[PDB]
Each structure stands twice: as structure tokens, then as C-alpha cells.
Length: 300
Length: 237
Ligand SMILES: NCC(=O)NC1(c2ccccc2)CCC1
Ligand SMILES: NCC(=O)NC1(c2ccccc2)CCC1
Image 1 (tube, rainbow over the protein chains, first blue to last red):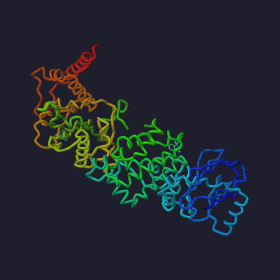
Image 2 (cartoon, each protein chain N blue to C red; image 1 turned 90 degrees about the horizontal axis):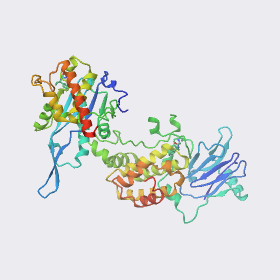
Image 3 (cartoon, rainbow over the protein chains, first blue to last red; image 1 turned 30 degrees about the horizontal axis):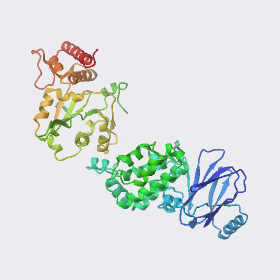
Image 4 (tube, rainbow over the protein chains, first blue to last red; image 1 turned 135 degrees about the horizontal axis):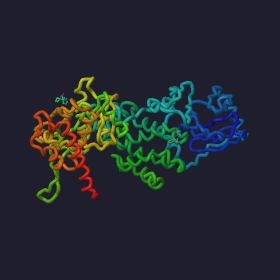
């Protein structure tokens, strides 16, 4: 179990760690988060009390280094940094634990929610979507646009998700126009899975990361990517059975976790109605259809 | 974006454009079977592809053999239309290719866009106008060449005959849409109006009669009367 200490908390902020959150008051003696489960990526995120504009945060994996948070009064945000002195860090952490100035990652033993939301998400893949090679962790905020959003403006601050476009030469084989547009299997299986992602685990990892950035930061571009990756599978007549079953599980846990009060903007009516009721895979997502119908029958 | 009443003069500017109407591509007669079920029989159809400035009509005849053994024919017809329009564009020299293609039915947008991906600079546009191009098969010479076709065939006509020698494209298009609107509204009456006077003939190389300017004003007034009549008849006014 690992620890992310905080130098201090000089401004009032709501701090999230994965699906958990807690309020810290201005200059409250908060010094970080302990008992973070090893084996998963994690995200530590921030919303300032005085300007809810810009939610922002950091994706990290404690197996890759010792990380801490320190507020920067010039740039006005909580920044993640890596401590390279291992003894300095263990000493800092031990002292804050002795003074009980840390919150405990509050994981119920029965609870597999975070695993289920991050099953295919790997730090190495995050670091290729979010390019900042000098750090081992990755910054994401509400405003960051995607490569695809940019094509339609600072490249270094972009989310480099895989571009999916159903009306593109990449998606449509010359001579198979109607076939490829109405059945996206060749774009899914040959172009994306075999060609770009290499396997379905990497595809699902990007899908899960897009969802989490949409939910945690209200990143509109991440929201578009998540729905595009769902639509591409649902609009394919030929999908491996293991992928459909796994997709059903992935989406079930995403819909379960989504705040009820955010569904109106995080759920695209067209995509979900098409996917659950019109697409080739309308009958292959039993768990997802059941939770959607009981939780969000309005959207549908 | 969409072509409507506001931007109507744009049709007659110097940017090459084509209207595509797919109404008459997939045509059937519905009938009873020996067992008392219903079946369809396809008949030959056509794509109506028109340059509104010049009157050039690329009439691609769709022979019933196209449909043999195919499913979901009304969906296929839109894609076959888009395939044939793309093929026409590719067959034209670069300086003759359109800068815009306006589809008369919005369901043609995605099929045509997908077929034209190789032409990113050709705009594919819908229209808010309710154009009467379905009535093209009420023009006797067009209907005759479609029904007689034994194989796929493209036939080239100017739909304005020689009108552009005397009138502008705007006026020619207005006359064409009036004639077609009338033929769509009441084909029998419209054709009576056009042929009542046996001394006015259709040249071998024309589609419409050889009216003088004065006779065209009369004819056009008669077509308006017909359209208003049929309106009152149908609507009781
Ligand atoms: N740039 C932030 C942003 O666009 N936020 C909104 C959003 C909608 C849908 C999905 C994610 C975010 C909230 C209004 C738009
Ligand atoms: N505008 C008639 C004309 O000058 N040429 C024709 C035409 C060309 C191309 C498309 C449609 C018609 C008449 C048949 C050849």
C-alpha cells in the first residue's frame, strides 16, 4: 500500500482520489493520502472552492516512483511531483503517518469498482495519449482538447486519442462503400484492432480512460471518444464473442458509477439508443441494457 | 449548407453544380400472387442528374438486372445512385467536375458523401426546395428511352432544348420547374395543355414543343392555372 503526501493545503479544495472525494479547508493540516492499492492506475483530482472552472488532476501508478503534491502559488494549482530521494520520502511519509495527518484510501473489501473501471488501463498507454515524457504521471483537465477536435490548438497540451471517423478513407475501402459504412467490422477488426491497437485490451484501455476523463474532469473531447469507441463496436456485425461480453461488463460498471445528476450531458442519446436498440449488437449487451433501462429510462 | 429560397441565384452562378434526384431509380409495380400474397416487380429506372445553369441532363438508366438477387432494394438504390454519380464525376475532365452536388432528398447525403471521399473539395448539399424532378418520367422521350433499355446506359440531353438562346438560366429553370410541377400535379391536363394545338411540334432533337415567346407566356399561365385548380380540387377552395 502506497502513499501520496501533500506538502500542505493552502487553498480550499475538493480532492478526489479515484471515485472518492473529500473537502479540505483553507490551510487545514492535510498531508496526503495513504493505503493506496497497489496494482492499479489511480487519479488524484482537484476542484478549487473559489473557482470550479477547471477540474484538473494527475494519473499515476505508485509502482513507478514516489509522488507527492505541492501547491504552487504562482501557477495557482496543486502540482504532482516525483521525489527521487527514497529515504527523504519514506521519512516524510512515516512522520505524517505518525501524526495521523493523512486520509486513508477508503476501499471496502467487497468492492471491485475501481478494478472494474480500470481493468485495461495502463500507465504506459496513458503516457502516449497524454504526452509529457519528463514526468511519470500525467496531467489532465476539463479544457484539454483532443487531436481530432483540433483538426476540426496547442499540440503539447492535447489528448492524443486514436482518431475514429466513420466517413473517412481510413474507415471505407474503395469499392466497399455501402458495405463498410453500414457494417463497420473491417474498420474495427482490421484497421483498428489488428492495425492500430494490436489487441482488444489496448482498445478497451483507451475506451476506459476516455470515460474516466469525461466523468472526472468534464472533458467533452474524452466524452466524444468514449462514445465513438462504443459505436464502432456496436456498428460492427462481426465482433469476437469475448469482446462483446467484456464490453458489456465494462459499460455496466461505467453506467453504474456515473453520477445520476450528470447523465443528461455525459450520455449521448443517439449513440445509446442506436447501440442498445438498433445496432448489430442490440442483443449482446444484456447487463448494460438492464442497468440503463432501470437507471436512465428517460434518455431512452 | 442547405440550399433554399434565400440563396436561389447561386444556382445560376459560374461554379459548376449538379442536382441529383434519385426518386426514379428503384421503381416497382405491386401486385397479387397466385396464393393471394403481394409481390413487387421492378421496372427500369433512372438517375436524374442536372446542371441547372446549362440544362445538361446526365440520365443514367437503371436496368432491372441491377436488382437481381439483392436485398433491401430501397437502401441499395441510394448507394447505387451515389456510386453512379461518383463514376460520372470521375469520368468528367477536371475542369468540368462540379464544385457542388445538391441532392433533392436528404437520405442521399451519406451515401454520396461516402462515395465522394476522394473529392474532399466537392460540397454535398441538401436543399429545402421541394423540386418536382420525380415528374421527369412524364416527359415522353425520357420515359421512352428508360423503358426501352435492355442494359445499363447513360443518355445525354439538354432539358432546356434551345431556350438559353433566348432566356437566362434563371428563367429556363423556372419554366422547367413549372412544367414539371404541373405534370406532377395533373399529368393528363398538363400534357393536354402542351399538345392541344397540333400546329406546334416537338423537334426531333427536342423534348418540349417549339413555342414562340408569346406562346410560352400563354403556356406558362395555363400551367399556373392548372396547379391552382388542382390545388382547389384536391383541397376544396
Ligand atoms: N469543455 C467542458 C464541457 O464541454 N463541459 C460540458 C460537457 C458536456 C458533455 C460531456 C462533457 C462535458 C458541460 C457543458 C459541456
Ligand atoms: N447541351 C447539349 C449539348 O451541347 N450537348 C449534349 C449534352 C452534353 C452533355 C450532357 C448533356 C447534354 C446534348 C447531347 C450532347
